[PDB]
Amino acid sequence: SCYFIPNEGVPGDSTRKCMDLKGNKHPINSEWQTDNCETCTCYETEISCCTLVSTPVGYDKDNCQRIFKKEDCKYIVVEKKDPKKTCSVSEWII
Amino acid sequence: SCYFIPNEGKCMDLKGNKHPINSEWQTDNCETCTCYETEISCCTLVSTPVGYDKDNCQRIFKKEDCKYIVVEKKDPKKTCSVSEWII
């Protein structure tokens, strides 16, 4: 899933570099990864950010649980009675 | 956004049609789908506008173009500016 918002650039600046939420300016047409598992792209007239995280939505919710691993921007899906055991996932969404 | 499911076995879609692997096809429903040897993936082609004047303006889907326009309720031929899209 992605959002797209206007690129206002930085008023006062002599260029339309996109500013991110943490105060970094980015070159027109550049991509960066954020600190919350997103990939963002700076364009002339817009900024888009898309999640890198695929969320598992189809699996045995009785016997299995999903656990988010921030550092790898992903989920694992594992047995409740023993999270060292992996379950099968029939549907992911991103 | 997209869903990803196992290809249990070319590949077959919900509507029975078979597709050559590594192929893309567009559905009846403004989705683009791909069959990989291992999995099936479908994503929407539609950007949904969500940031706009909702008292004065409305969004109207155009299915054939898989796109929205956002226009004035009092005159749907006049466009309103949008500050955010989501896909």
Image: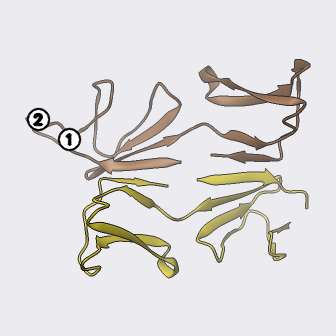
Chain colours: A brown, B yellow
Looking at the image, do the residues carrying marks 2 and 1 touch, with CB atoms under 8 Å apart? yes
Rate crowding at label 1 as few (under 14), some (14 to 19) or many (20 or more) other CA atoms within 10 Å.
Answer: many
Q: Looking at the image, is A79 positioned above or below residue B24? A: above
Q: Which residue is mark 1?
A: A9
Looking at the picture, how far across and down is residue B53, in whole percent? 27, 59
Q: Secondary structure at mark 2?
A: loop
Residue in view at x 74 percent, y 43 percent:
A57
Callout 2: residue from which chain?
A
Q: Which residue is mark 2?
A: A13
- With B35 as the anchor, is B47 left or right in this view? left
Amino acid type for the residue under numbered disc 1: Gly
Residue in view at x 52 percent, y 78 percent:
B63
Quarter assignment of residue A15: top left
Callouts 2 and 1 on one subunit: yes
Marks counted in the figure total 2
- Distance CA(mark 2)–CA(mark 1): 8 Å
Residue in view at x 51 percent, y 81 percent:
B64
Quarter assignment of residue A17: top left
Residue in view at x 39 percent, y 43 percent:
A41
